[PDB]
């Protein structure tokens, strides 16, 4: 078959563990044709690792979208998007396209811009095939605030699904539990808990981007949403376990570890 | 051991077949840790496919370099660079790093009748990049420019160009003959200052080759990083790109990219090697 065309709308992580770098690397690992519409460029100070986010002008953002839409993506992912304007356009781009899958990683950084959260709820959730919040982001999107348990994650997932997302996976992460990694997946009918072990020498920069990018490529290549999130969780678990130390401040996931090194078991249960 | 850290200094090809996209994809296929310092963004009109090159401001270029250099590349590739200033910086970044390998893809545009679009850029490459290069990877046109010989038409002309490019300081030179040299076979000429080798594969379909050059240079870089000799890196890189070209696909009426992952996923192609 021809390679599936998979677009990410995301920024450049110059360190190359997260951002569009994670997305293109993951798309490559999963035998898709990766494409990116760049939103911003993120750099890091050599001594302190302080981040500098340089937005790209809207005119060049729009030129890239014209090109990507002409090529015709089969699936679109959104990464961290910085403005309500870009959030709104990302949704519009997916609706204009013939893409069948839209995966939204609702990256946020009390939230820094609650305006962006409101924009995600308005413009992206109603279009999303899968939305992939971490525990914090899920509390923001659902309006519940802080989530502390699987039962709280069930409530938030219901609310997010009701806002229009077709499938919701909330990543518990270290915020939920420091010995096991628990995610709550909801399809409108059934709550599934997905669990992987955690490992001592792991590194996690780019994990969220990688998970969402793998989900997108798995969907594009024909996995059901359930199968895609379960396979994506195994994919990123391997990446995290095999992450490596970049400097005193960070270490990226190994995007290629699933294929090159090992698979990690994912336990699936109904909750 | 640890993944080798491989940096490209290149622009974004929004169509994703060439540019930094080809570089990161190839880096990933070859089990390295790919990185980019972005110079520019190239977009295309939906109707005519006319290109628009949007330079990135020099301050953001510099911020990316600082981050990349802090991380510490094991190898650096240069793709198409738009100005003498960025050509010069690229060479400086390599000197400042602890990278042992520098692969320069000396991308130029021919204006017709063997004339180059930006002659200052060719002078800047000869001045700042050739003397630093582990490998330089010109096509036939570029090699005529870098050597000052103009149009090359034979292996004998290519040998002459290679010796001149070597004398300008490149450690290893590979001149890609392409369709300009022969329509049935893809002949490249490799030189290491001592021996000339002709590398051959079949000339595959010509329709869907977008990103071939970038891919070849990126693969060379990755193979070096991962410990292949320069001769084995270029032979391996030739095989790698040959499968990519053979398995290219039609994107639209104007372009078709190489399949960067074809070597690993689809098939392996033999490279004939002969001393000449």
Image (cartoon, coloured by chain):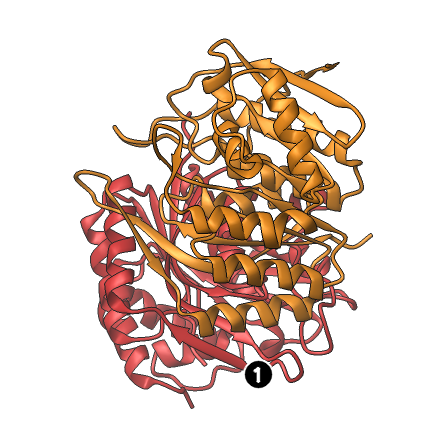
Chain colours: A red, B orange
Task: State the residue lying farthest toward the top.
Answer: B184
Horizontal placement of B129 versus A170: left or right?
right
Q: Which residue is mark 1?
A: A50
Where is residue B62? Give x, y as percent. 52, 71
Task: State the residue lying farthest toward the front.
Answer: B149
**Residue drawn where x is 32% and y is 43% of the image:** A73
Task: State the residue lying farthest toward the bottom.
Answer: A110
Viewer-proximal residue among A186 and B146: B146
Where is residue A228? Give x, y as percent. 48, 47
**Residue drawn where x is 46% and y is 18% of the image:** B179
**Residue drawn where x is 55% and y is 28% of the image:** B262
Viewer-proximal residue among A245 and B194: B194
> In the figure, A110 relative to A29: above or below?
below
Crowd band around label 1 with a 10 angstrom C-alpha radius: few (<14), some (14–19), many (20+):
few
Horizontal placement of B44 versus B91: left or right?
left
Q: On the image, which quarter does residue B94 sit in?
A: bottom right
Question: In which quadrant is the N terminus of chain A drawn?
Answer: top left
Callout 1: chain: A
**Residue drawn where x is 55% and y is 49% of the image:** B125
Viewer-proximal residue among A24 and B211: B211
> In the figure, A41 relative to B1: above or below?
below
Q: On the image, which quarter does residue B275 sit in?
A: top right
Residue A228 appears in the picture as rendered: no
Residue B123 appears in the picture as rendered: yes
Where is residue B211? Give x, y as percent. 46, 36
Where is residue B109? Give x, y as percent. 39, 39
């Amino acid at each position: 078959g021809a390679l599936k065309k998979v677009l990410t709308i995301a920024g450049s992580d110059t360190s190359a563990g997260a951002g569009m770098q994670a997305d293109l690397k993951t798309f490559q690992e999963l035998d898709t044709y990766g494409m990116v519409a760049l939103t911003a460029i993120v750099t890091m100070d050599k001594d302190t690792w302080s981040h500098d986010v340089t937005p790209l002008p809207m005119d060049v953002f729009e030129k890239q979208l014209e090109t990507a839409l002409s090529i015709g993506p089969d699936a679109i992912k959104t990464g961290m998007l910085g403005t309500e304007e870009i959030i709104k356009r990302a949704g519009e781009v997916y609706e204009a396209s013939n893409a069948q899958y839209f995966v939204v990683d609702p990256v946020m950084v009390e939230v820094l811009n609650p305006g962006n959260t409101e924009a995600m709820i308005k413009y992206l959730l109603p279009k999303a095939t899968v939305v992939t919040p971490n525990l914090f982001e899920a509390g923001q999107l659902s309006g519940l605030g802080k989530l502390n348990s699987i039962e709280d994650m069930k409530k938030a997932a219901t609310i997010i699904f009701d806002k229009g997302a077709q499938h919701v996976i909330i990543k518990g992460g270290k915020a939920l539990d420091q010995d096991k990694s628990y995610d709550l997946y909801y399809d409108g009918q059934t709550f599934y808990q997905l669990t992987t072990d955690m490992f001592q020498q792991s590194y996690n920069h780019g994990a969220g981007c990688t998970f969402a990018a793998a989900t997108t490529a798995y969907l594009a290549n024909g996995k059901s949403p359930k199968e895609a999130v379960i396979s994506a969780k195994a994919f990123v678990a391997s990446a995290i376990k095999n992450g490596w130390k970049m400097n005193d401040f960070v270490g990226p996931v190994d995007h290629g570890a699933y294929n090159r090194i090992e698979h990690i078991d994912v336990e699936v249960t109904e909750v």
